[PDB]
Image 1 (tube, one colour):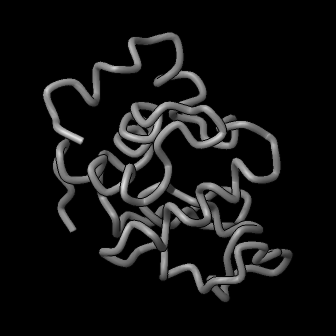
Image 2 (tube, one colour):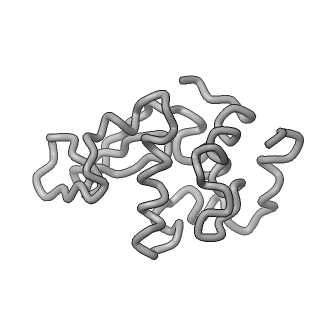
Length: 129
């Protein structure tokens, strides 16, 4: 799914990420754009041997089973391609879980240093929710 500005976040709010663990929805609409720039299918090789899957670029290294990974943990107990599905609840529902181990949103590199330190509201301005 080619996700537009308006389209991704209207769902991330109906995906139950709005102010989840306090992180405002704009963190979710920015980090989605810096990990995958709203691409639901983009999957990238990690150098250590795992792969990044899902529009939230969720790393198969321990989160999911992609079947090409010795030393993978699947805490999210889903096959890695689910994260690729046109439905955001595949990605968003283990996104909560990643924040659900209490290590913040510092899990992601793109929010980590490219999405922090900014106006949060600026992704969600002029789009109705």
